[PDB]
Length: 153
Image (tube, rainbow, N blue to C red):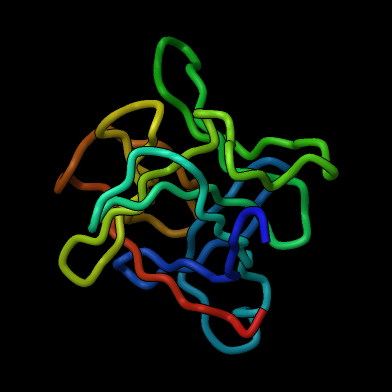
C-alpha cells in the first residue's frame, strides 16, 4: 500500500484522555469506564521525512475523518489546530510540512515535536478539561509526554 497507517488513542503522562471539544479543538481530561468511548481515535500515518532510530515522522488525523493535526503561526507564535482536508487526497506519503510530527521515543514515553517548529511539542495542561496546545517548554509545568494504545482498527 502507498502510505501505511495504524489506529491508536493517546494519553498524557498524567493519564488524561483526549476528546474533541469543539469542531476544531481537542481537550484533555481524566476519563474512566463508560466515558472512555468519547475519546478520539487516531489514524497515525508514517510519512516521508528525516528519520532516525528514535525519531519517526508521522501525520495524525482522526480515524475515518478528514481532520488532521496541523501547525501554524498565530500572533507570531507556533499554534496547534485541527485542519480539514480534501477526503480524496489524504492521507499521502508526502504530507505538507505543517502536518508532520516527529514521534520521539524517550524513556518509555513518546513526545511529538512539530517538524515545522523545532522544540515545540504537543502539550496538555495539568488542569482538567483544558485545550491541547503547542508548547515550546520542556520539563516545565506542562505535560509533553505520552503513551499510545493500539486499537484493533
